[PDB]
Amino acid sequence: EKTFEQLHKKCLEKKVLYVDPEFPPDETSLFYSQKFQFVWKRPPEICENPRFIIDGANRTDICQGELGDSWFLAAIACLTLNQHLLFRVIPHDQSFIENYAGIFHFQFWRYGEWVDVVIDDCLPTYNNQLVFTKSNHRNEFWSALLEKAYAKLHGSYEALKGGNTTEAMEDFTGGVAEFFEIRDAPSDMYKIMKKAIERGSLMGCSIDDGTTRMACGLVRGHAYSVTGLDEVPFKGEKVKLVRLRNPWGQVEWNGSWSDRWKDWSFVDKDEKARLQHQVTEDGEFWMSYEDFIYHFTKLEICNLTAD
Ligand SMILES: [Ca+2]
Ligand SMILES: [Ca+2]
Ligand SMILES: [Cl-]
Image (cartoon, rainbow, N blue to C red; front, side, top):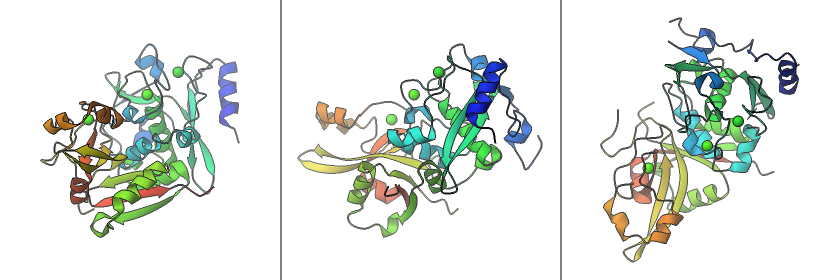
């Protein structure tokens, strides 16, 4: 069939913007169950200087919109902790300012092989803003486009409503997903999680809802990304910590080790820097290992295939 390269070249020669026949910018690509609201617009119509990737592809670029696909977004965020893996999914040679023909592509691991998914860059908007996933930088479009490509792989945006983080992790790595009930967690699980993150394995977690917020700042039935583990010295003892990211890009733990916790004052300025401590409402936060195990019920690890 026609490769991305073939289609891209063709559009450039005809000086036309690609329109995807198989996943067109209309209601069919949005939903399946019902017929029901959004204007489709390409990023150069949304803003004056759109960019595919600004300041690197990282986890601050993944902010959930009006679609319940946290399971997928938590996994993208995890993937950005591992830049060399990330660039297999997101081909870097793509631009709005050079050889632009309104066509992009992404690679996913599917039937024991990398498959290429091609999309046009039309995206759902309302009042000229993205309604679905966006970057916290208003001119950056890779994450919105990746979501679109993944929606195409599943037939519609609506098909991304509900899923398991481990499905996305496998689709991005070709690794093998493993589950832990935190209830049955062994004594050394801090160490297990630490070794996994250092190995570049993707890790997500959630609080089971038997399938809007909690007082402590956590969200039930919601995929979080595990983005770090570390030990800090605090009042003469070493304290084990866990870092998580809510793929909403906001709404955080408000307990100990949270952003605004006063007893951060007792931590040395260099240690703060090593932990990348920042008081910012970005969805990312430290919490104690002890509080983590106490609130979270499910931990999912995707182990990279021993090449
Ligand atoms: Ca970025
Ligand atoms: Ca924060
Ligand atoms: Cl660009």
